[PDB]
Each structure stands twice: as C-alpha cells, then as structure tokens.
Image: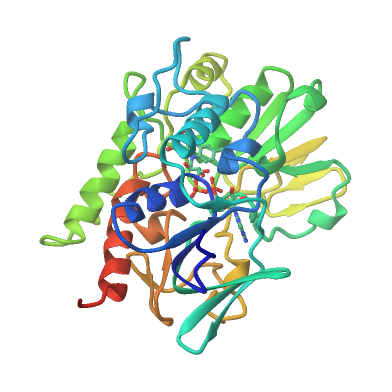
Length: 357
Ligand SMILES: Cc1cc2nc3c(=O)[nH]c(=O)nc-3n(C[C@H](O)[C@H](O)[C@H](O)COP(=O)(O)OP(=O)(O)OC[C@H]3O[C@@H](n4cnc5c(N)ncnc54)[C@H](O)[C@@H]3O)c2cc1C
C-alpha cells in the first residue's frame, strides 16, 4: 500500500480532546494528516485527573463536535473515567490517523515546510496545529522562601487522593473550580486554609458550567460585533456548586484569605502579622501552555504564551494553537468550547493549503 506521504499537509501535535476535535474537522477535507500523542493510549490530561473528579456540567454540555458524550447511567456529572472512555470511543468511531506514544521534541522551519521531530522519528508538514494542553506545565507563583518550607508541597497536577493528607493542616492556594474542589475534598480529612488572589465568586446553586460557556460566548460575539463590555467583568472562572463544593459550604469550609507574603520553615507569614503553621500546601495555581516543542522557534514569550490572532500564530507561517485557554479563543480549554476554534482552525488551514485544479 502507499507509503506515508513524504510531506503531510497537516501534523496535529497532541491526542486529547482538542486534537481529536481538530481531527474531526480535518476529516471532511482532502488534506493528509497525522496526530502525534505522547501517551500510551487515549484520554489526554484526564488520565492525570484526581480520582473523584467530575465535570462541572452534564454530558450534553461536555461534548466535542460530532458524536456526543454518552449520558452517565449513575447520578451526577460525568466522571474522569467517563471522559476518558468518551475520548477512547470517539477515536474508535472515527479511526483517525494517530501515532502513540510519540513525544514531539521540536518543530523546525526548513525550506517552507515544518519539520516535526520526536527523537529519531521526523516528519515534514505544510501546516502544524499544536493541541498539547496545559497539564504538563504546572505553574506555582514565585513566593519568597518556598525552598525553606519543610512540609509537603504538591501541585493539583499531581494530586490524586486525600489520604496522605489526613489529620494534617493543609493550605490550598488558588481559587477557581479546581481550588474549590480540592479544598472541599481535603477538608473532609484535614484542617484547611484557602488562599485566593481575590475573594472567590460562586455561581448559584441551581446552575452549572453552561453559564460559564454562555459568558465566554457572549465575550467572543462582542469581540466581533460592536466590541465593548468591561462592566461587568466576565467572571469566567466563577465556581460551580458541584456536590462536594455545596457540601463543603455547609461545613464552613469555603472561606479564603488573600495571599501571604512568604514561606517560613514551618508555614507561611503575611505582611500584617498573620502567621500560620502548615504540614502541606496544595498548589491549585494553574498551568502554562505545553509549548516546549516551539521554544526553538523563539515564539514562546516570558508568559509561556505565544502571540496569536484567534488560533493563528502571528510570527510564523502555517502554525496554529488550539485549545490552550481563553487566550486561544474564549472557552477553547473546555470540552464544549474547543469545537468553535477547532472548526475555524481547520478552515484556515484549508484556506492556506488548498490548491486550484
Ligand atoms: C482539574 C481540571 C478540571 C477540569 N474540569 C473541566 C470540566 O468540568 N469541563 C470542561 O469542559 N473542561 C474541564 N477542564 C478543562 C479542559 O477540558 C482540560 O484541561 C482538558 O484536558 C483540555 O484538553 P486538551 O485536549 O486541550 O489538552 P490535553 O487533555 O492535555 O491533551 C493534550 C495531549 O497532548 C499530549 N502532549 C503534550 N505535549 C506533547 C508533545 N510534545 N508531543 C506529543 N504529545 C503531547 C498530552 O500528553 C495529551 O495526551 C478541566 C481541567 C482540569 C485541569
């Protein structure tokens, strides 16, 4: 049968939801393409989510393009394992060209093509779409004295179960949905403190993450009609009152302080005299984009982000970034929201590559 094409039209780097949704749209084109994903099997970063994690909206509101997420038969929003299974079944449905396990090291512009390199294995492509997520680049803010702290430090990226924290005094740093959920779970076994940059904001009890998607969509539509609305703010990471978080609220757990000033050997200290000893800190302080494979090109800013117009990289030809965060399209880092930019990305790749008869 035919060899792999010496030049692929498109390489997609990654194999999670964003890559798959991009693959869905590429399948209605005539372009040759290939997905390269570093893990042994399907599931993207959901493989690394903590054991109890569930989505903040129902299945219907957590679907990527095409085949929708099966409704769970047990009560509650889809679990981590539900998402993994969804993605696994979605790949089985469409038989996308995916190679695993392939860790892309770099991307090199050579002659007017992209050379994509994973160790020994290299491919050439006319276009490269990066959809590598964020989980592999946990971010911790640069607080003084962290190196001195003698208790446990872990990022949420590495959290799985609350067991080893039981009976301890634990600080959760970071708001949003992740902070609130991790805090809620830790508080069931440990004495907790929550640190957030701003006072946390909660959605009403009767609503779900579809509200956050609406807000996102309203923002991009305004960014694109008569563009305005600084007031009110987006509240784009207001907290959804998922069951464990609603239970935490009843126990008085959802109260936060503003950031401390430094770490000591035994805990933290604020500029105003607050001083708190801690056995462990769980950093729910977010992530940077997983763009190490673009560093040699020089496009990754001090931010860790890259200058883009929607998903198109500004400084370089025929490169797109899909699904990383609002900075690559409002709501693009969610199951429901990635579709809009995966779709428009595929159209832009077509526009760049299709040739007259
Ligand atoms: C704790 C948590 C809770 C969340 N809750 C929700 C929710 O309730 N609802 C919702 O819609 N979204 C939620 N999200 C957000 C978003 O949907 C997830 O972050 C999701 O994993 C993003 O999918 P992605 O495809 O962009 O990235 P990923 O799932 O990270 O997929 C990227 C894939 O590319 C691979 N890869 C990375 N670098 C390379 C490389 N160099 N070469 C080859 N492969 C590479 C990765 O290993 C991975 O398999 C949550 C995220 C987190 C962290």
